[PDB]
Amino acid sequence: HAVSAYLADARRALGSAGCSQLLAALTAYKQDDDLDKVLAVLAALTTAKPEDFPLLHRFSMFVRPHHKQRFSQTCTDLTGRP
Image 1: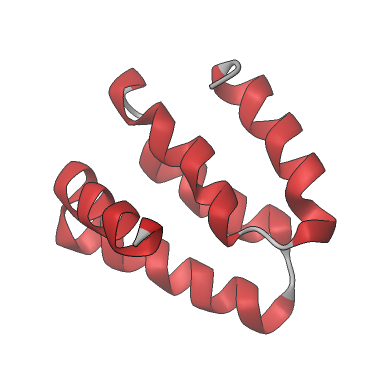
Image 2 (image 1 turned 90 degrees about the vertical axis):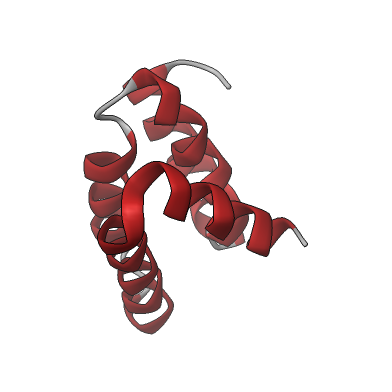
């Protein structure tokens, strides 16, 4: 139940509107395969406080195999290694 644990943590840290924006961006990503767009929503929401940085890295669970390397590189440039 990694997904429900992520959604519980994200709704707690980001609030309902922020969690809803993250899930809408995930929906859009599954439709359009645009990694940069989903990453930009996620980074706006999860890098405002250092304590939310793990929610940036943990989003990798939803990132498609062909984008996981680039996603991990960008998250490390934003926040360091997890």
